[PDB]
Image 1 (cartoon, one colour):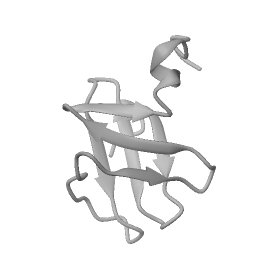
Image 2 (spheres, helix red, strand yellow):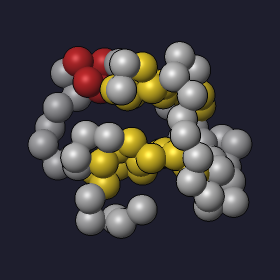
Image 3 (cartoon, helix red, strand yellow):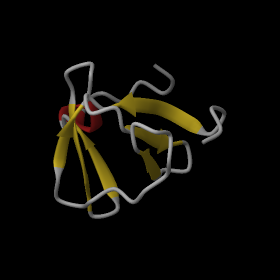
Image 4 (cartoon, helix red, strand yellow):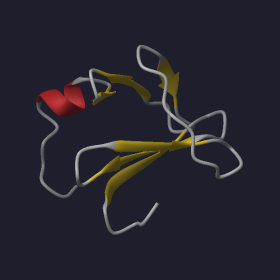
Length: 74
């Protein structure tokens, strides 16, 4: 995964994990730490209570986090 090239990792309520990379892509793993492709068009939940989806090679993070949630860092 490399924690150096990821801006934020998302832990799914299912155990699976998503990472938004500093290169702009995203990587998904299952509750067993194994890498698998993230299904486009599907909105999924996190343990933290956020909803996310991969659409058009992008990532919706409640959408509005992309809207006005640009902080540069966090």
